[PDB]
Image (cartoon, rainbow, N blue to C red; front, side, top):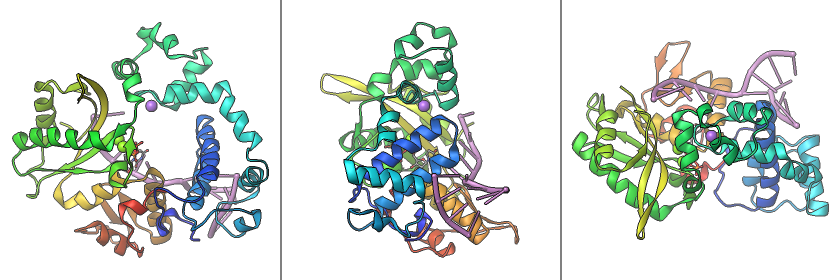
Amino acid sequence: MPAYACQRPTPLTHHNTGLSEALEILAEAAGFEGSEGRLLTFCRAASVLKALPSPVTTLSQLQGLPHFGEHSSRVVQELLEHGVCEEVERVRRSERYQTMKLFTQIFGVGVKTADRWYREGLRTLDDLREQPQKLTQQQKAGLQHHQDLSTPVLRSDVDALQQVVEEAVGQALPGATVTLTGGFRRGKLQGHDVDFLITHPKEGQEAGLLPRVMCRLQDQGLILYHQHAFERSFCIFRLPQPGSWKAVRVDLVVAPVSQFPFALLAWTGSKLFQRELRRFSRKEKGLWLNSHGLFDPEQKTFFQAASEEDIFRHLGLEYLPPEQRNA
DNA sequence: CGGCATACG
DNA sequence: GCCG
Ligand SMILES: O=c1ccn([C@@H]2O[C@H](COP(=O)(O)OP(=O)(O)OP(=O)(O)O)[C@@H](O)[C@H]2O)c(=O)[nH]1
Ligand SMILES: [Mg+2]
Ligand SMILES: [Mg+2]
Ligand code: NA
């Protein structure tokens, strides 16, 4: 079992679901307390379990696995012995965890805002609605639409959206293309949002595109919220439903075709997979990876990639399709 | 011990 | 919290 998640396939469904979910609760709780390092270790240990070929049934099977030390091993030990880990259950029912989860789930509210509201005594969404003067417009939209945004987006919803985005993109710039990224590209059946990547085959033609796309979607009455030159937009869309509609989060990113493999890799995820790949690139290969390119800081050169396959090869890694990047 | 991913809105 |  290699130490980095980008060195091993991780499928969407696996054989250690209960154990991985428990460790992810502790990772989430560590993030709420500001401990990025603890969050990473618990996330990494969970991801190791997702990569195993069969269920863990005995503690001895953790011996030698990366990211299992005294704490994560004890958690697994208790789940194997009793079906429950007391530390996890204590976190689950705690007011701090439940409120921080509730608040950070809001579009426009992160850990720091949630923590400040928690310390001020706020606990419920109606607590926030009663003091709307303390909310940004983004937070107001996230709070108004919170119920719909709490409903999973279905793969059935994604096809309909991609068609309307393609129509607007085609009027804004004929020949421009729309690619589904994020969790749906990794094979997820549900999501919290829909993520799209837009480009054009002629380098440079994509400049100025996203404002033209957003103006056209807004004119069609499909935009319930957006932030407005720019190249990323995090929006709330109106999606049709039987006799009505629902609000859906949609993310649009524009990249030049020269950078498209890097952007596709970066926005396909998973989040942990990309953090691990970027850490691997820098620490093991001395190369700096981001959504624009792969930089050699010694030669001061960028690696020209024509595909995601090219990027894995340049990092010395076996290629993983998106469905195996579910770290 | 240091390190823990990344850049745009 | 764990790795190197
Ligand atoms: O902190 C972050 C968030 C997101 N991303 C990059 O953006 C992509 C989309 O980020 P999303 O938050 O949309 O996640 P997801 O699609 O993987 O899962 P859902 O909760 O939406 O079902 C992620 O898969 C990752 O590639 C990061 O690199 N870092
Ligand atoms: Mg997504
Ligand atoms: Mg998204
Ligand atoms: Na949030």
